[PDB]
Length: 60
Image (tube, rainbow, N blue to C red; front, side, top):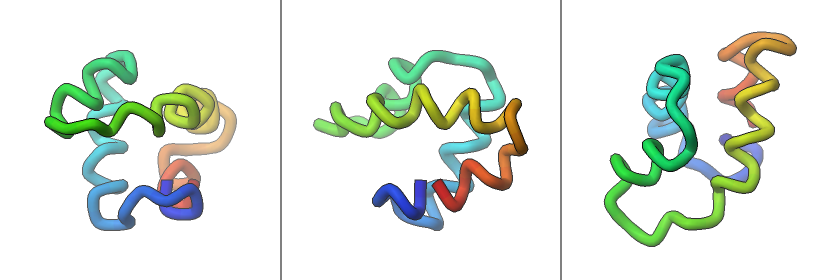
C-alpha cells in the first residue's frame, strides 16, 4: 500500500478492514470517493497476507 501509493497512516487502518475478508468493493465503500483504481492492486495484496503477513501488506 505504502510503496504503491496509499498513505501509510490510512494503510494500517485499511488493512484492518481486509481481515474481515470482504471484497475490495467494501473498501471503496468506506473511502467515499472516486478511489476506483487501487482495487487492481488490492486484490493481489490480499494473497500477500496469507503468503507472508498483514504487516508486509503495509509496505505494499
